[PDB]
Image (spheres, rainbow, N blue to C red):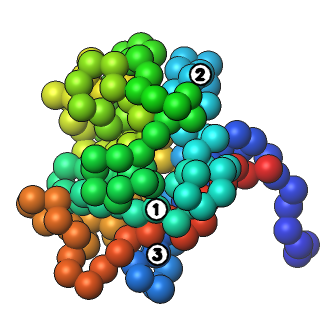
Amino acid sequence: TQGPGSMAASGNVYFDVYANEESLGRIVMKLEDDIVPKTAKNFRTLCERPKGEGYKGSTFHRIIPGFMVQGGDYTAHNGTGGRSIYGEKFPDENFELKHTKEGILSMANCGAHTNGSQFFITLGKTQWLDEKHVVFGEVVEGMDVVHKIAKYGSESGQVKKGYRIEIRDCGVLG
């Protein structure tokens, strides 16, 4: 029996990731709204907003094989920018979730209580980040697309010359 099914997964968000004009595929993330509601809200909202006001059309600007891939700087594209939906830096909501495995979605920051819009996805267990970065979700489809992203990085985090690794579209399923 053939045909598409309706949506099970509501609230899950996705990134369609591109290396220049080549599709790398889709990453789908589950957010832990019950555990970190404001952190989850910030990220989901930034997925739904238009280009220039959220993640749509932004890049993975720091890509470190064996460690993590980082994006969310949709204003400066270099790690110095980004803005949360609250208008500025927001507190670490809690550290209940831990960096236990590959595919963990966590907030980038520049110290205690400095959450904006930058995030990373881990390429392994990174226990040294526990209690320093707020974990708010995980990759549930397209972990292999995260490993593809890593092919375009380096020890230093610099992205391969000639490449922009872009979140070409993003949103909420539903």
Query: Which amino acid type is shown beneath numbered disc 3?
Result: Tyr
Q: Secondary structure at mark 3?
A: strand
Horizontal side of residue 156 vs 57, given as left or right: left
Q: Amino acid at mark 1?
A: Ser
Q: Quadrant of residue 44?
A: top right
Q: Where does residue 4 sit, x and y in percent of width and height?
A: 85, 68
> Of tags 1 and 2, which is closer to the observer?
1
The residue that appears at 23% across and 25% down in the rendered structure is: 111
Q: Which residue is mark 3?
A: 18
Look at label 2 and name its amino acid.
Pro
- Report the residue at 56% width, 51% height from top: 54
Q: Nearer the viewer, mark 3 or mark 1?
A: 1
Q: Nearer the viewer, residue 51 or 132?
A: 51
User: Horizontal placement of 61 versus 154: left or right?
Assistant: right
Q: Is residue 139 above or below residue 170?
A: above
Disc ID at residue 79: none
Expressed as whole percent of the image width and height from the top left, the position of residue 32 reads: 56, 28
Q: Which mark is residue 58?
A: 1
Q: Mark 3 to mark 2: distance in Å?
A: 29 Å
Residue for point 46% across, 85% down: 22
Q: Which callout, 3 or 2, points at the residue further toward the start of the chain?
A: 3
76 left or right, relative to 18: left
Can you say which quadrant of the picture contains the N terminus? Answer: bottom right
Q: What residue is shown at x 24% (from left), y 59% (from top)?
A: 63
Q: Mark 2 — residue?
A: 37
Percent of width and height locating residue 53 = 58, 51
* Cα gap from disc 1 to disc 2, whole angstroms: 24 Å
Q: Secondary structure at mark 1?
A: loop
